[PDB]
Figure 1 (cartoon, rainbow, N blue to C red):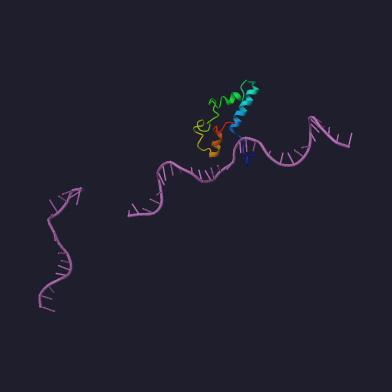
Figure 2 (spheres, protein in one colour):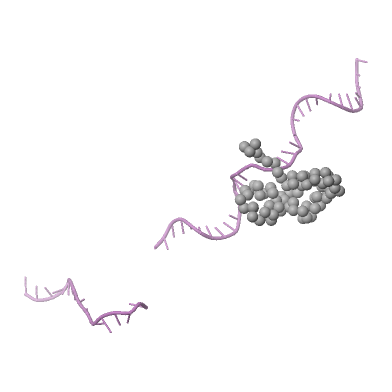
Length: 74
DNA sequence: ACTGCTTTCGCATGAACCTCCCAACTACTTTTCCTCACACTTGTACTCCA
């Protein structure tokens, strides 16, 4: 319900839904072949809030823009 | 009586204040997000004691 929805999205989600598309396609890429392509600054997991939108940034509140960049690693 | 004691007055034109706020960079909060390992049971393992 839109009344107090509290949607559960994190940067751990956008890798997890990117891992499941790899096993339905039956790919040899894994979470060792994801954490080696994100912590080596290859696909934009880290620092995503700050450089990606460039026009949609400013009206987003402070705790929401905190979650969308690559804050920690999982 | 007479002084001091006033009072108008001027060659013609050109022109020649102060407190509070918005500063600047510090620091110490806000605005709700995500991420989970913790309490008592219960079921299942391999002992038991009569």
